[PDB]
Length: 296
Ligand SMILES: O=C(N[C@H]1COC(=O)[C@@H](NC(=O)c2cccc(O)c2O)COC(=O)[C@@H](NC(=O)c2cccc(O)c2O)COC1=O)c1cccc(O)c1O
Ligand SMILES: O=C(N[C@H]1COC(=O)[C@@H](NC(=O)c2cccc(O)c2O)COC(=O)[C@@H](NC(=O)c2cccc(O)c2O)COC1=O)c1cccc(O)c1O
Ligand SMILES: [Fe+3]
Image (cartoon, rainbow, N blue to C red; front, side):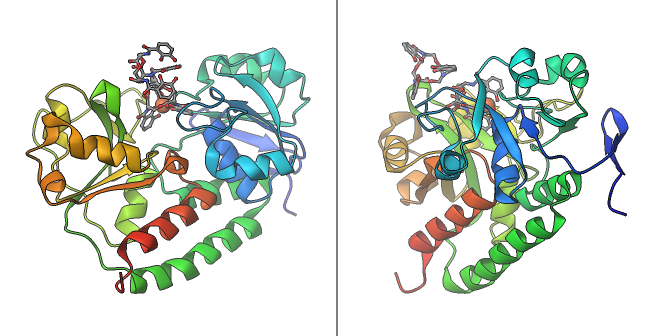
């Protein structure tokens, strides 16, 4: 039989007696993947409504419409609340290990309400994460279907586009802060670009970020002099940004000497690409096609 089944965490192996039917996600990031495979996620943590990466509820933009259609409940905005979770009467609770949406501090408390699992999204492809969530929820078939849909579009996409100059740097840029976070090869963003045939730029020395003690594997912070130093690719991709962000880079005196700037190879991928799940991955495909189709 399919249930019960054991799922192993960083906190050991746990028993899911039966298929979850009321999943609460304390990670707004994880929620996108849950929705993509039609898992019964009935409530989610949210970030700040109408901020750079979220909709009017604090949900991530790429699955905003889906959450509204399904009447997804919002647990809280920003600060995690164990009582809010309890009130949803979950039979499974998910927590992200890293990121601003991690409710890891409430692990012990949440653990008393329902079986509770800790998931990393900082160190694996969106497909890997989807597959893992499929095992957790009993929606393996759905996860495989979503991945197959993408694989078909990818096979066509790789044929349809001509790559810009390599290697490339992928970031999230914060214009008024004159800073960026640089996506690593391990990050979902990095793995996706590699899958599409891109080579990520190697970093200078002094650039390397501790990821001991379970610290995140997805980004390297670029503040101060590290900004110009870290944007060293021949092309530059801005996730979670659109044209005004690319134009801000093109106009920044601090960055004027960089090759991606001087060769006009700075590309915005969209505000809905802060986190990668099936929905935003498909968007990234479409955008790369719009930018790089041979015939353009
Ligand atoms: O100080 C922290 N945020 C700031 C400052 O961080 C930022 O300026 C940007 N941010 C990254 O570039 C980033 C690139 C790659 C990965 C990132 O996570 C980025 O944050 C944009 O983030 C934001 O727009 C918002 N962001 C989310 O809603 C979010 C939703 C779900 C999950 C999140 O992690 C979110 O940020 C609001 O957050 C913030 O602005 C902060 C500290 C410690 C660890 C954090 O993760 C922080 O975010
Ligand atoms: O680009 C925007 N800002 C700039 C310029 O804003 C600011 O420099 C500061 N901040 C205010 O001055 C502010 C005064 C009055 C009101 C403010 O909201 C201020 O933030 C510091 O904020 C931060 O550095 C970062 N950000 C958070 O960590 C955050 C974490 C939790 C919650 C936050 O709001 C955060 O900003 C990066 O943000 C930016 O630097 C920007 C865009 C879209 C929506 C935004 O909210 C932005 O601020
Ligand atoms: Fe964050």
